[PDB]
Length: 162
Image (cartoon, rainbow, N blue to C red; front, side, top):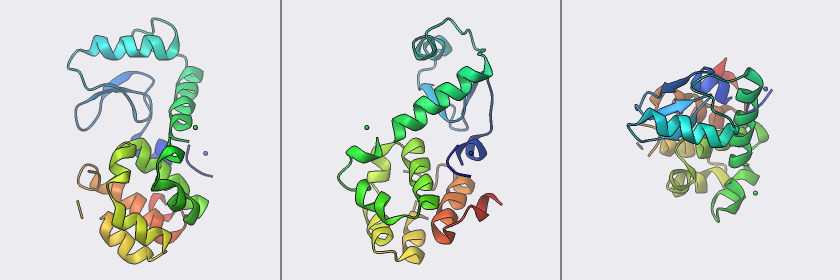
């Protein structure tokens, strides 16, 4: 029971392309296609990502596959960062999937942007690390999801997702 069996809890699951809560166009679980107003750009980037003219619908196995391609993009992506790697080491794997949720969500740069919270995580001052993951580009964006993930750091378990 881990990241897949986390984000799938985090974002629901539609085979169809759809708007995210921030209004960026999206298909699958958290898989941004384009920020562009044109949906066709989303369908086209989807056309490259899937290798076929999906036109907003895909076989569920392709959804699982693209979902794996994105989670794998998160896993050659967290490692390159100078800051995230020691923190990814300090986390229990149950929190490591949470860091994967972070880098998958706000992007690697924003997860890089919470340097103090991460410093508290590697030092395992989990409480203030949580209070600092709480002073907001992420926590303000998805406050319930961010609460679930920060709780995931607080607990060492999936309990926020209950």
